[PDB]
Image (spheres, coloured by chain):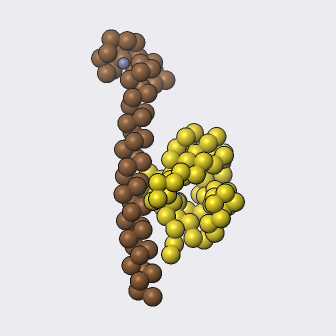
Amino acid sequence: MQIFVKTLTGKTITLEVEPSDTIENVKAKIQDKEGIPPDQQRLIFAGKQLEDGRTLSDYNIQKESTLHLVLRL
Amino acid sequence: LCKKGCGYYGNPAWQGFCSKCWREEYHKARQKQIQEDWELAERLQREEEEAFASS
Ligand SMILES: [Zn+2]
């Protein structure tokens, strides 16, 4: 299923994911696509920073859900 | 009957809304969640800017 990841520059990244994917595995997909090391990525959905060992389904991330991404400086 | 009162029949799989009122409700809820997430992200960015500055 597709999800979108928006940055603070207005850029949106589309990812192909499954609800059982771990947050760590979504960070790897973002690194593959945008070059950002997983350790510099902070993901947000619904008022929460997303934790690496949890899944997209734990956060009710569904088809065409939009996450945000902030980078560690 | 659609619980928004548009006159169409509601679908129990759509929480009692008809198709059109359900899609409106879905879009509005995602728009609000996406705006609040953006505000949180700007707050996290400011926190990153402070920590980075402090070193
Ligand atoms: Zn209706």
Q: Position of residue A20 (x, y in %)?
A: 65, 48
Place residue A26 in its image quadrant. Answer: bottom right
Q: Can residue A57 be seen by looking at this rendering?
A: no
Q: Residue at x 50, y 47 (%)?
A: A66
The answer to whether A42 appears left or right of B37 in the picture is: right
Q: Quadrant of residue B31?
A: top left
Residue located 69% across and 60% down the image: A32
Image vertical order of residue A58 relative to residue B27, above or below: below
Q: Quadrant of ligand 1?
A: top left
Residue B12 in the image: above or below residue B28: above
x, y (%) of residue A52? 60, 63
Is B5 placed above or below A50 here? above
Is B20 left, or right, of A16 in this rendering? Answer: left
Q: Is residue B17 left or right of residue A52?
A: left
Q: Nearer the viewer, residue A67 or A7?
A: A7
Chain brown in the figure, letter = B
Q: Residue at position x 41%, y 54% from top?
A: B37
Residue B8 drawn above or below residue A38 = above
Query: In front: B33, or A60?
Result: B33
Residue at image point 42% right, 61% down: B41
Which quadrant of the figure has residue B19? top left
Chain identity for the colour yellow used in the image: A
